[PDB]
Image (spheres, grey):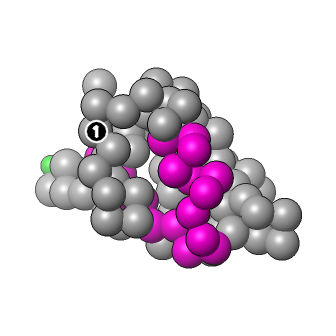
Amino acid sequence: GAMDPRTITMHKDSTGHVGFIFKNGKITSIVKDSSAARNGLLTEHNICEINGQNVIGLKDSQIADILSTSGTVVTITIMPAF
Ligand SMILES: [Cl-]
């Protein structure tokens, strides 16, 4: 149902970005026309896995560094959170 996970595969743009903001593991904004926008990354969902790597229990700075250092393809598993 509503709590099935979603896998969102994005491609960094020419500036190195997939197009989102997050805080405390939770997506908070999507950049217009970005890969995040076009592949359905959602706010009010938490980041669980990036490129197959479990990121549950990691700090935002750790998530950030995984995102920045990734190759162009960035795949995120997201779940609703409360
Ligand atoms: Cl449901």
Q: Which residue is mark 1?
A: 56
Which quadrant is the C terminus positioned in?
top left
Magenta segment includes 34: no
Report which quarter residue 36 is drawn in.
Answer: bottom right
Q: Is residue 40 above or below residue 2?
A: below
Residue range (magenta): 63-79
Residue beneath the point at 32% across and 65% down = 52
Q: Position of residue 61 (x, y in %)?
A: 54, 31
Magenta segment includes 65: yes
Frontmost residue, 66 versus 18: 66
Residue 38 visible somewhere in the drawing: no
User: Is 18 on the left or on the right of 51, as rendered?
Assistant: right
User: Is 22 on the left or on the right of 30, as rendered?
Assistant: left
Q: Is residue 8 above or below residue 54?
A: below
Q: Position of residue 47 (x, y in %)?
A: 39, 44
Q: Secondary structure at mark 1?
A: loop
Frontmost residue, 62 versus 50: 62
Residue beneath the point at 64% across and 39% down = 21
* Residue closest to the far right: 15
Which quadrant is the N terminus positioned in?
bottom left
Report which quarter residue 75 is drawn in.
Answer: bottom left
User: Is 76 on the left or on the right of 20, as rendered?
Assistant: left
Residue beneath the point at 38% across and 39% down = 46
Residue beneath the point at 19% across and 57% down = 4
Report which quarter residue 22 is drawn in.
Answer: top right
Q: Is residue 5 above or below residue 11?
A: above
Q: Position of residue 42 (x, y in %)?
A: 49, 50
Q: Is mark 1 within 8 Å of ligand 1?
A: no
How many numbered badges does the structure rendering display?
1
